[PDB]
Length: 153
Ligand SMILES: Cc1cc2cn(-c3cccc(C(=O)N/N=C/c4ccco4)c3)cc2cc1C
Image (tube, rainbow, N blue to C red; front, side, top):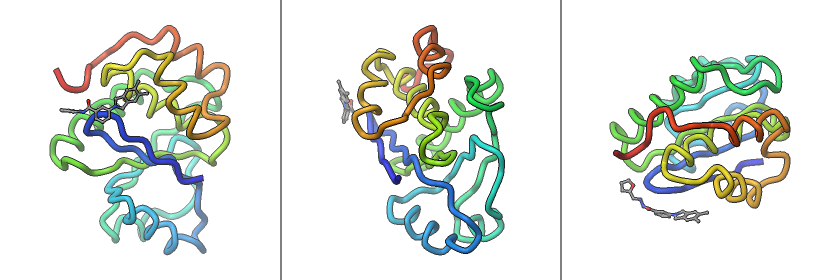
């Protein structure tokens, strides 16, 4: 389920998980939204060689099962956001697991919070665009989440 999220000057795309045989359609869906980077939060699957060749960099930072992202992944994710939108204004960052496990959306949620949103509003903003956005462990994480590096001053 391709779902797009725009807040301030940030844009994110929560995609499905393609297979090697459907990568050409996937790449053109990404380009459609001007996606220039992809973060895989679940065990690797399709081969990235082809995607990269098309100008889309793939980042593999899996969570351990449905557990909240590690501090290392949260740090790198927030850094990616900060650098990508500052070096490529207007671009889009894609993130995905399998379009239903409620893992990928947390990353978008965290970006919204650091961007100024209340975790409550960040969750409703996403939940309204798609179901199964956050598993139980995920929601609790966001509830107790305190900003580590705000986006835009
Ligand atoms: C309650 C609620 C309020 C929302 C307000 N916007 C929204 C939409 C479009 C633009 C901006 C915005 O501030 N521009 N950024 C500017 C900027 C300058 C530098 C960096 O960024 C904000 C999405 C929302 C979603 C919800 C759910």
